[PDB]
Image (cartoon, rainbow, N blue to C red):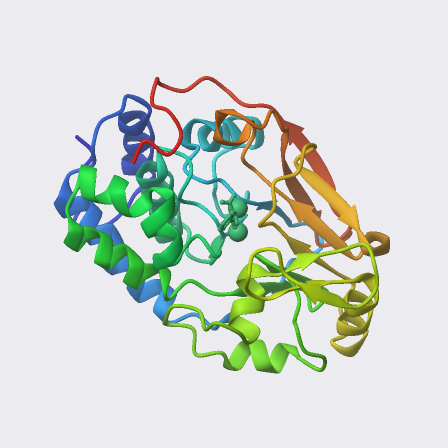
Length: 312
Ligand SMILES: O=C(O)c1nn[nH]c1-c1ccccc1
Ligand SMILES: [Mn+2]
Ligand SMILES: [Mn+2]
């Protein structure tokens, strides 16, 4: 079984872990525990807004929702290469729920965050919250594989996940989207005290829950919290904060991505054939320091073991 080397994640352990998980085996509770406490410490020290500089020769890969589709997560790393200092990643929330290999996804992602803390980035989604985990399978999965106490620890680690990432002061990445009120700025995002369950309304809620709409202005959300926001909302926010565009995730898309609001609101979704039912393609994005324009890479689902969606 995979073991830490002097209580630390190594590239060797991560390879063993991914193979262990491919073969439907469980990471020992002590190792899971250690990954969680160590990554909690890493994440707790980060700003709510992660601000990353991408030099002219450097690239980054942005992935959207993964939703416990562990075998598709491995496929991303086979198509795009494993994470490293020279192949950095952002995973933009919704790692868990729906898919029945959520534990394997999230421990794999936290492992890589510990191995490459400055080059492997995790942003919180609305599915990294208690109400979602309780309904949509992650709580059950953690209780089935480990204990109720292990779940409380996951919840507490999720609370320290940052809420957005800004690349070169120009691309802003969040899970959900923009805001239900006008005049919200990067300063406000930086100052969100994020170690909690999201409020019923406010900036923290919007970052996890909001959705673009084609028509101008805002609308009440079909989801019951946050809002739908139009092209004029995006345009104004970006002009006021000196940004080029936003990358969001949150929603399933048939092509794995959507380019909305005149090129200014991009969706990226990385869970192909969502819940073994939707038949959508997935995508990941490349960005370069010399060119911040998104390059999309589409991909289709790979086989996984016979465990149905939402089993837990
Ligand atoms: O479940 C999903 O696909 C999802 N991804 N982001 N938000 C949701 C969601 C949350 C609550 C109810 C329905 C969908
Ligand atoms: Mn979501
Ligand atoms: Mn989602």
